[PDB]
């Protein structure tokens, strides 16, 4: 077999790229113009920073002025005061939304890693990744079945009677599994160029796993073999078996990045709108 | 122990049909959808003494609340101080048309916003009817009764009248009901009633809410997703196969069963099968009646996502219309 | 009998998407908001000063009388509302230019996507009529014995998988190709074994607009069907074969021989390296970029309409 096992390894060894979701970062801060225009409309008390220098210069053609010190300067100010506040109070929402995405992506990254490696220590092959071959692949004494992606490449790919079909029944092959990890990866780690994670790719891998579920050897939701996920299955759902649940939790956090993406793009457009709104309000002060 | 994977596929499809599509999961918040009260309140301001009265009955905007608020709009809702919310300069009149332009546009958008909501309401209910039409033979799917199955001969083997795939239940009933019993489909999977070729849909109903137990305990608190429908078909097509049958009209890969059969309208454990060759003529699994309804529901669930994008965009225009109204209101505050 | 249909249907789904039209106009809304709003151009002349008001710097009088069904009075706003309109005027001027580039970017992206679909089905971006250039020899298209032009086209893999001597409705619900028999690659014989084999797919086509997800979905369908666990000797990776089973060659005489052994063409175990899936991915990627550019297009149209609203607010100062 050995098809969904290495496939899930590539999906767990994908690359979460926060930058490909956050995107612009240029319109996210409060537009400099709605801040420069604001100061020039501060009447004759608050205006009198080293930033007044950048304003009233850099015409960019070959841009700003102190308007009439009448009520129109304050009349324009109260118009842009909300425009100034709206950008600043929207940039915080954009920044908070970015932190939501960054938390979700890494959390989905942790779930993707914790699905394969232990916690997040996949930099080196911990021995806790692989367990005994009676309580982890058979689950007799303790119900510790099918824990990780690599916790299943031990059974059906160790012991005897196999012509690399999956490229110590009862005992623990922890070190042999550590060696079998090197042999197994050699038939893997090709990756898929690590393009990006996708919630559909997790469901597709999950669905592909459900296809290979089944075997007609001697001791129903199984994959000799020594797998028998029915040990910890409890109710038939794979929502109990660990690595499927960890993959699903990662998809749930990854599902939220698109929702914040639609919110985030529209908020940036509003900032671009608030720029154009402000210039047509500086004319209020003639 | 025999037809376990096939049940897992059908139970997966049943799960989505048992899932509910709440309308508000797509419509969302509607407190900002209507015409903003700020742009309305600003419109009463730039009106002068004339046209500002209850007796303007010939033209009234939303003054069915007997006006009243016309003079009470000038409130004091601010910070520790009171600032917000009208003389009668030429700027007052010149600001009215600027508000009137956005006052119209906000109201038009409110109608357009409501129009997109009605599209979502219709599509979701139309989609909801489709999922039901797969689980039952109706758009309601209420009582596990009322004969939404058919005879064994017609529904499982397609001998008399080609009626395979009519409902996900019929395919579940045929696959999990035979004389020979085991943990074939589920734990309590014997299905003794629906055994003979003459076995009517009543027999299936009598052993329906006994083999469907695990499925209803496994439907989780999620919502149907168009990928979930396509996923449900993927596990279904993966399980379709039984290399043993009746030669002609035995196109396998269209058989949901096991072992030598020669029939699926019988008592043998093997006859716990459904041959679709007599319905899947075109050659596609997607021609099974509950597959099309699954795809019909998934298609409608993709349509509401786009209308949601239109709905969200309209509320953005409404909100920036509210801000632009204050800009036009600042025209009047000129000496 | 039908012994490759599970493999055939996966290939037929891809052929269905390639035989589908993207309709370059479905991703555009209208040519109303795209051009510069004439009202802003109209309001430009109502405050276009009194000098340069009819001085066309190489007409203006016809446009100044065009406004017939307020007054271009010489006040401050005649030069104090023009500046606000000027700021808006060229902002919408660049915006409509960017809109035109976005439309051209969409059209170029859809054509490149549509070319890729034709490239996967046929080998060229012009799927006009069945040509011998579409297929190649068994040695190349199916068995990989002599050259590695294996996954060139879906059309060659279909002809390799659904054509052999021994074959009763091997797939396609009607007949089996009887000329592409063994070393006789005869790409012309694969052309004779084409219209008979491909007629079911020319009925499975529907009004399903070519979508990025459907292309990735059909690839998953092919992934499931990719397998032949018996096959033959070294460099015969059994997971990367598409056939009945228990063979030693591909496209020979046996129905089993109707197989495609990508082992020689494939590398790093990535099916996303067979020619047709590559093009399918290229088409899917470009189609996604169409969605992104269309999202920009509607956003730009939104900014143009608000610019026109700002024009009156700027122009209302002249009263
Ligand atoms: C894009 O917007 C800019 C905004 O300035 C336009 O630039 C002006 O174009 C007018 C055209 O008659 C010239 O007279 C000005 O000298 C330009 N000013 C500057 C600062 O560039 C420009 O025309 C717009 N369109 C394009 C294609 O650039
Ligand atoms: C924006 O936030 C400031 C405080 O940071 C607050 O004083 C102001 O009222 C807010 N205005 C808006 C429009 O949100
Ligand atoms: C819709 O727009 C038209 C434009 O003439 C306007 O007369 C009408 O009042 C608008 N709708 C509403 C509900 O205001
Ligand atoms: C299913 O039922 C048949 C007929 O009784 C039996 O022969 C098989 O052994 C069983 O699995
Ligand atoms: C399916 O049923 C047949 C008898 O029809 C039996 O021989 C097989 O063992 C069973 O799987
Ligand atoms: C190819 O399939 C045919 C069916 O027509 C069978 O007769 C052969 O044995 C097989 O190789
Ligand atoms: C495929 O063709 C081989 C040729 O030997 C035959 O043995 C198999 O029975 C058939 O399916």
Image: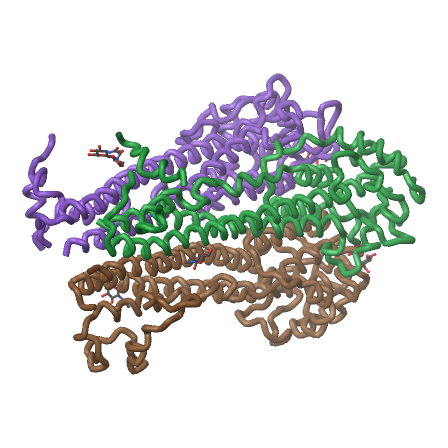
Chain colours: A green, B brown, C purple
- Relative vertical location of residue C224 with respect to residue B78 in this rendering, above or below: above
Which residue is pictured at 63% across the width and 26% down the height?
Answer: C266
Which residue is pictured at 81% across the width and 41% down the height?
Answer: A129
Quadrant where ligand 3 appears: bottom left
Which residue is pictured at 61% across the width and 51% down the height?
Answer: A253
Residue B128 pos. (x, y %): 52, 65
- Along the viewing direction, whichever of B141 and A127 lies nearer the viewer: A127
Residue B157 pos. (x, y %): 65, 60
- Along the viewing direction, whichever of B294 and B226 lies nearer the viewer: B226
- Relative vertical location of residue A59 with respect to residue C200 in this rendering, above or below: above
Q: Quadrant of residue B212?
A: bottom right
- Is residue B283 visible in the rendered structure shown here? no
* Count of numbered marks: 0
- Along the viewing direction, whichever of B273 and A283 lies nearer the viewer: A283
Left or right: residue A173 versus residue C213 is: right
- Along the viewing direction, whichever of A228 and C259 lies nearer the viewer: A228
Q: Quadrant of residue C64?
A: top left
Residue A92 pos. (x, y %): 49, 51
- Is residue C230 visible in the rendered structure shown here? yes
* Quarter that holds the C terminus of chain C: bottom left
Residue C153 pos. (x, y %): 52, 29
- Relative vertical location of residue B152 with respect to residue C148 in this rendering, above or below: below
Left or right: residue B175 versus residue B307 is: right
Which residue is pictured at 70% across the width and 56% down the height?
Answer: B8
Instruction: Report the residue that reaches farthest toward the top.
Output: C146
* Quarter that holds the N terminus of chain C: top right
């Amino acid at each position: 077999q050995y098809e969904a096992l290495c496939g899930a390894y590539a999906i767990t060894k994908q690359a979460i790229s926060d930058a490909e979701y956050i995107g612009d970062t240029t319109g996210d801060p409060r537009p400099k113009e709605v801040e420069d225009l604001y100061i020039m409309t501060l009447s004759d008390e608050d205006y009198n920073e080293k930033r007044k220098s950048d304003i009233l210069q850099r015409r960019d053609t070959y841009i700003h002025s102190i308007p009439a010190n009448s009520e129109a300067r304050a009349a324009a100010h109260v118009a842009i005061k909300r425009l100034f506040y709206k950008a600043g109070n929207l940039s915080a929402n954009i920044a908070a939304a970015i932190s939501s995405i960054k938390a979700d992506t890494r959390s989905a990254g942790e779930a993707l890693n914790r699905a394969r490696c232990g916690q997040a220590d996949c930099k080196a092959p911990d021995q806790k990744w692989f367990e005994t071959r009676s309580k982890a692949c058979s689950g007799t004494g303790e119900q510790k079945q099918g824990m990780t992606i690599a916790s299943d490449i031990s059974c059906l790919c160790s012991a005897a009677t196999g012509e690399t079909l999956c490229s110590r029944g009862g005992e623990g092959t922890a070190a042999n599994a550590q060696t079998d990890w090197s042999t197994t990866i050699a038939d893997c780690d090709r990756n898929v160029e690590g393009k990006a994670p996708s919630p559909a790719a997790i469901e597709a891998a999950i669905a592909v796993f459900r296809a290979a579920l089944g075997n007609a050897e001697f001791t129903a939701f199984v994959l000799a073999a020594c797998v028998d996920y029915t040990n910890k299955l409890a109710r038939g759902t794979i929502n109990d078996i660990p690595w499927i649940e960890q993959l699903r939790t990662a998809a749930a956090k990854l599902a939220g990045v698109a929702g914040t993406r639609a919110q985030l793009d529209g908020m940036r457009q509003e900032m671009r709108i608030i720029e154009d709104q402000a210039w047509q309000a500086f004319a209020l002060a003639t």
